[PDB]
Image 1 (cartoon, rainbow, N blue to C red):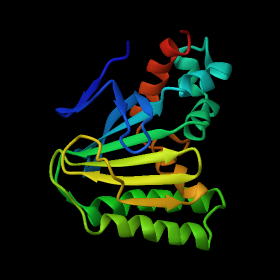
Image 2 (image 1 turned 60 degrees about the horizontal axis):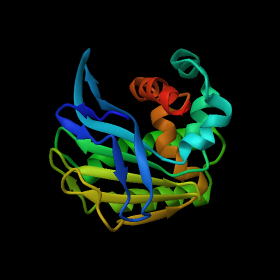
Image 3 (image 1 turned 45 degrees about the vertical axis):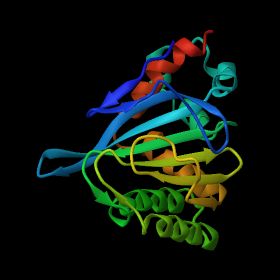
Length: 212
């Protein structure tokens, strides 16, 4: 009953299933990301956020019967999405070929920013971020290539790279650290998140579901 979303010709299936956890997620939102070079916005990748099907039951309690605008304006709503007792899956597909180290540099920057910001950037998180970086080094993302972030509610971040746009069956690395595990999503729909495109999709699509 939920639609799919195509971003720059890169398609995001309405629903999906993890070959790693066997769980099922539904599309929460999609969008684009890039760089602004002298006023001009140059797109580089498409991003999508999937929420485990059980996420609805969880969110029902506090958000069933809210308006797409009430949601969009309430931070607590997104905190619940970020740190909800379910798995979240984030798929980044490239529009412009970037190397593993190239792509990772910025996101890692935002993750460290968020972590030092909320006072949770210790030796553990630093090392976790080095492992994070380490996993991208041997990789390259030609157009259409994807990166999958599996955010386990158990404080683990699953990392897997795909040559195309389908979910790889094995994960490249597992980052075991609570703070870091949510950092990535935090930089996309958190309070201090730039581009509201994903927040808007979430606020627009969830209401329907939270009623059935």
